Each structure stands twice: as structure tokens, then as C-alpha cells.
Amino acid sequence: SGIARGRLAEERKSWRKNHPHGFVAKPETGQDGTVNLMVWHCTIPGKAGTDWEGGFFPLTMHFSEDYPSKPPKCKFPQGFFHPNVYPSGTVCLSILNEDYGWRPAITVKQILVGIQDLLDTPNPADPAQTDGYHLFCQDPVEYKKRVKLQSKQYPA
């Protein structure tokens, strides 16, 4: 099946054996029922005691046949509000940078946990959207309002 699909089957097996509470990660189900190992639909829970609490944020992971030598692309929905998320939804996380961050042994769980931390602890060196980044830097009161509001968009 090739290297990528072999690794993704290992990632699936490990995830199903042991993953953090409240997270979801699985290969997408295609229209006819066939599972596609190359695109995973994941859910990252907000941490209790942060403005992300109570939210369950949908994150899609997109793998190529170049994986795991090259990183996946991770996306929240278009319009998602966060300093490090592009208007398209793409997440800017330093381990997803092929040249300046990625290591091929990093697991799906390790990626999802890194993104979870990124929610309440953004990386100020990676501005990716004007809305989220401008509020975050120098307007903490409005930023907080916006994050709390967005968590209500992602229940359950």
C-alpha cells in the first residue's frame, strides 16, 4: 500500500489503543462508505479553565504519499478565529513546517496535542490572519470576547 498508508494504519492502531480524553481522530468515510486513510477528521477539545472551554473544534488532517517524510496539512474551518490560523483554515504550527520544523516520527496524537496547546497559547511569531492576530497582540479584552463566542459555535 506504500509507506504513507502503512504509517497511517500504525497511527490509527495506536490512537485507538490510547488517546487523550475528549479527542477524536479517524480517517474520513467517503460517500460510498469507503474509508480514506489520507484524510482524517479530528476533534480537539478546548481546555477547561480557558476561553476555549466547552468547545470541540473540528480539525482535518490531509496526508500525501510523501508522508511521513513530509508533514500533513491541518485545517480548521474557513473563518476560524485564532492568531495562527489562515483565513482558509490552515493551521500554522511550527512542526508542520517541512523545512523548519517537521520530524517524521511525530505522531498524529503529538500533532493534535500541539494544536490543542496552540489554542490558548498562540505563537506570536506566526501571524496568519489579520482578525485574530490584531486582537490578540494589543487588545486582550476584545480577543477574549471573540474566543468565548467562537467556543459557543462548536458544541458537542
Image (tube, helix red, strand yellow):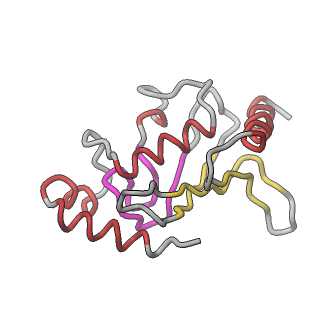
Q: Residue at x 41, y 35 (%)?
A: 94
Residue at image coords 33%, 65%: 147
Quarter occupied by residue 125: top left
Residue furthest to the left: 138
Q: Residue 59 lies in magenta, yes or no?
A: no
In the image, residue 90 lies in the stretch drawn in magenta: yes
Image position of 111 (left or right of 152): right
Quarter placement of the C terminus = bottom right
Task: Name the spot of residue 115 as percent of width and height, x first.
Answer: 47, 45
The residue that appears at 58% across and 31% down in the rendered structure is 70
Q: Which residues are magenta?
A: 73-92
Where is 14 relative to 129, above or below?
A: above
Position above or below: 15 against 83: above
Magenta region, main secondary structure = loop
Q: Quadrant of the N terminus?
A: top right
Residue 85 at x, y percent in the picture: 39, 54
